[PDB]
Amino acid sequence: DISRPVCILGLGLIGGSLLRDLHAANHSVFGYNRSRSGAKSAVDEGFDVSADLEATLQRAAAEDALIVLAVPMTAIDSLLDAVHTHAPNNGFTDVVSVKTAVYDAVKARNMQHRYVGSHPMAGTASGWSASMDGLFKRAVWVVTFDQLFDGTDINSTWISIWKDVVQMALAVGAEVVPSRVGPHDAAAARVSHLTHILAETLAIVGDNGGALSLSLAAGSYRDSTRVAGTDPGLVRAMCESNAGPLVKALDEALAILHEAREGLTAEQPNIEQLADNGYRSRIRYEARSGQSSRPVLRLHPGTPNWEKQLIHAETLGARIEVF
Amino acid sequence: DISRPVCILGLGLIGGSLLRDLHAANHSVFGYNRSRSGAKSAVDEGFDVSADLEATLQRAAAEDALIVLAVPMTAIDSLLDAVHTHAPNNGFTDVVSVKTAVYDAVKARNMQHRYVGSHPMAGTANSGWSASMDGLFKRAVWVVTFDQLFDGTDINSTWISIWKDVVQMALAVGAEVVPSRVGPHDAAAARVSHLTHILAETLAIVGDNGGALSLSLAAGSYRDSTRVAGTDPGLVRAMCESNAGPLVKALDEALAILHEAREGLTAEQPNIEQLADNGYRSRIRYEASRPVLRLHPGTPNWEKQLIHAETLGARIEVF
């Protein structure tokens, strides 16, 4: 279980849902919502919430709480600065879709000895009314571990923060997948950010078709343009934060689409390669989900060479369980 | 309702489902399936299905039945030859996802005087008779063609009666009938269905190129946007290859947007304002249903109202 009380900063879809699940699971937890209304609402429903950021961090520091920065990327720096200044010895984690940008921000402030990156594959970062129960059940929750393999010189206290973050993610039914920042952003660029870019693109090309096109659109179109409904502010945050790895991903998309075009413009139009490859890839994805077959490695923090199992899990996309 | 009994050639998702609804609605209906096994299954469930193509057409000839070609585009060219030889007087339609190729195949064989093209947006499936279902067309769109009124073509009251029964059949099984010519249809289908497939196959591969971790981290958005990549490649090829010209027009717009986005992400200060905004705004329009137009075939300039429905993407009902 979790050796520290959890302190959630920001109580929206992610943070609120985390507070609720942790409370359900009966673990010590409290949090902060900027909204005076939202705080009052949660306190009245039974939760331990405040709208006083200074007071929350003072207490967080007093109880050595694990601090969860459950805010959007644009809010991270101010919350890092707030934590650095009010709970400089506390351990802490974030929930943002992109990881390199955050780790960098943490390193620039010399907070890497107290930080463990994390990213739930939950929904779209909406305030407190967005919070629900069991959001994370059987959902992937990435937990980082760069400090173990880069130029950071960490000791046992960091290992202790890392454990609580994993115990926390596991406490709310998540599947913890360990990853360093580069491999993660490389993945998210492909499976989430490009997903969003293609979704916007499709909506425009369809809209360009006018009345008949929007009328004839069916289930496939509904599904492929759904995430184009998410907020422009967020879609930009994701993609811009991770522009580097996204461009590598988008370039693969353009190469494939160019090859596809070469094929459709031939004397005999042909897209075998795109079709056989696409199908096969989609089958591989379904195979390790539903119509969850992720492998599972058991780490034993403390034991020699356990760290190498984190890289082994990263390469395999294995979820982990710590004994 | 429908004046003629229905004859369904090919009984998979589309044709098989069309049979079940017309049978449930207690309308006169019978069909054909190449698969001898698939025909036995149907007969063993109480349906009027045969494996003998020639005999099915001779029966369709003796009932003046409406012939529905519910087969893939690759089986069309020989089926037209078959209907020509064994049932020339019969009025027929089809359900293929591309409408130009079929109409050319029809004209090539001088059959357009008894042909009314159509396309139900009912999707596809990796199966035959076993994929059939009740209520497949409820609320879904059913496109019906009418190029014969605007290209050079001498038509009589029969064609109109054939067109009337195709619309009513569509309506009978709970579909919304949007009329359209082959050019506009294929342009639209290129944009909202075929490009959709192309983009899904692409995303699936890019994600797979990322290896174990990428696939493991893929969540809801990926799942939804790569769903059609799971449809059998053969169907995807047929669908896109048959509509190659229009699809390229659509793909080129996609590529324009995607490059302009890459310009955006490579800047000193990465920026995809434009894409996100236009994208989001395009989706909001889509969500917010189709307009309607009353039509009486025969009355002067009723065909003008078909063009109106086409521009509007409106569904029609017949008075």
Image: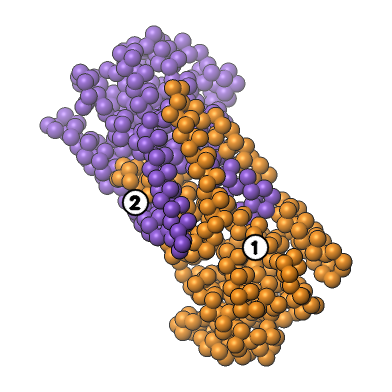
Chain colours: A purple, B orange
In screen coordinates, is A81 left or right of B191?
Answer: left
- Locate residue A225, reporting x and y percent: 55, 45
The numbered disc on residue A288 is 2
Please identify, in this view, whether the residue under mark 2 or under mark 1 is nearer the observer: 1
- Locate residue B77, reporting x and y percent: 54, 76
Image marks 2 and 1: residues in contact by CB distance under 8 Å: no
In terms of secondary structure, where does tag 2 sit? Answer: loop
Residue B162, compared with residue A24, is above or below; it is below
* Chain assignment, label 2: A
The numbered disc on residue B171 is none
Residue where numbered disc 1 is placed:
B182
Image quadrant assignment for residue B216? top left
> Mark 1 belongs to which amino acid?
Val
Q: Residue at 66% across / 57% down in the picture?
A: B184
Q: Residue at 61% across / 65% down in the picture?
A: B99
Q: Is residue A62 visible?
A: no
The single residue placed furthest to the left in the displayed view is A304
- Locate residue A241, reporting x and y percent: 43, 27
> Mark 2 belongs to which amino acid?
Arg
The residue nearer to you, when weighing B275 against B2, is B275
Q: Residue at 44% across / 22% down in the picture?
A: B268
